[PDB]
Image: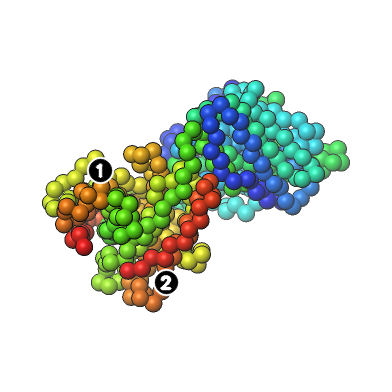
Amino acid sequence: EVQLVESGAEVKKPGSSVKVSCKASGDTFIRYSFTWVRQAPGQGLEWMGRIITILDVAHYAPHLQGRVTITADKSTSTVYLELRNLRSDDTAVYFCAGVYEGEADEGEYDNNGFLKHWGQGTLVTVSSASTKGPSVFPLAPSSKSTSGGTAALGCLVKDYFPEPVTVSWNSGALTSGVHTFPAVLQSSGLYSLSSVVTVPSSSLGTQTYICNVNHKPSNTKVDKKVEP
Amino acid sequence: DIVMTQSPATLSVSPGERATLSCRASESVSSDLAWYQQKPGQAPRLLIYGASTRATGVPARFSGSGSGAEFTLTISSLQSEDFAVYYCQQYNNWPPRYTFGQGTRLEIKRTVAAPSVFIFPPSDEQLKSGTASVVCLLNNFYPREAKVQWKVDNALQSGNSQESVTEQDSKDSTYSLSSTLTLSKADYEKHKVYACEVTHQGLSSPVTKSFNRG
């Protein structure tokens, strides 16, 4: 079975063209067919096209025909998706996916239409707005709800563009009770997002808490140590 | 174009009960129908193909059924970790021009849980930037319906706050909500009492959290 690893998030101006890569590792490349599925924010899935790797032939969705191209290079086990003359409606997460088709290099093909293996996706933002790194502000734990009991704390990742931004705690060690909210588009047109976490309050003075923020689109990677 | 319809677009069924998701095609697709499960911030996961074949590593509670134009997805013992949007996809036509239904969001209808409230003052670093963000948090509650009221010196604020809600937790089926009041450092400093008044079914009466500037 293959493991698909897609390229990073991208911002693209309306009318430009985007090319997304997908690296496949594992099984024999040519024994797989690959598909690109996209999902506009808050919307369902849209099948884009599929390439029959072995024959190097691809078919596409009627509405995207003419401005989309899917390619695959056996030598690098990489599948490519090229979308041209981008528009606002093209803003979405683009997913790479595939399925084993049998011993294709030995005369057989199942022509499976379903998708078993998926990539992590790639967010593509069609916009003319400027990329901007976020500021990371700490949410101080002075906030006590339970009798001592439970304390809350977090980080405010404010004014960045475009999406996405990832947040982790203690380099990934703290995952219990963590709630990272969906990004929100502010009045400014810039995004903001908070990541909070509840921990036993009797540990504020002994346990160190740090949020690990990353906005790859602007090469901004920050670590904010939160203190009460 | 073969249209795949999934209705309701949303369903709410109790934990431990059996969920029945629906999918129909604008025309016959025989048994070339697949089901996918997509959890928050995750890529779809193949559940069923050939209309009724469980894919590798898929629990037996997930069952495919139907053929032609009418299909059904069943999850016999709904758990918290089952929260997701389920999609059906047909792949019976040729040339290969497959289409997906628009999914059904499956909410786990757990018991009511009151929210735990926390209010956060602006950090000092942000204040240097001439802007102040006051954050209120409603943690692990159910149902999703919640009213957050901001008051500055008992003055009920409005149109100057934004809220964000997490998706149903995969462990306890609860939600978490953040309300962020935004105002100029200038406006902030000429005030003393900031309050967050929460209202939720699990609460006998409105719960408020607050702090005094400084």
Extreme residue toward the bottom, this view:
A206
Please give the name of the residue rendered at 17% of the width and 52% of the height, measured from the top-left corner: B190
Residue B93 - label: none
Q: Is residue A88 above or below residue A222?
A: above
Label 1 is placed on what type of residue?
A: Asn
> How much space separates mark 2 and mark 1, taking CA atoms?
33 Å
Q: Position of residue A195 (x, y in %)?
A: 40, 56
Label 2 is placed on what type of residue?
A: Thr
Q: In the picture provided, is B64 more to the left or to the right than A134?
A: right
Which residue is under mark 2?
Answer: A208
Name the subunit of mark 1: B
The N terminus of chain B is located in which quarter? top right
Please give the name of the residue rendered at 29% of the width and 50% of the height, measured from the top-left corner: B130
Q: Position of residue A75 (x, y in %)?
A: 80, 44
Foreground residue among A132 and B172:
A132
Res A133 seen here: yes
Which residue is under mark 1?
Answer: B160
Disc 1 element:
loop
Res B112 seen here: no
Q: Is residue A79 above or below residue B191?
A: above
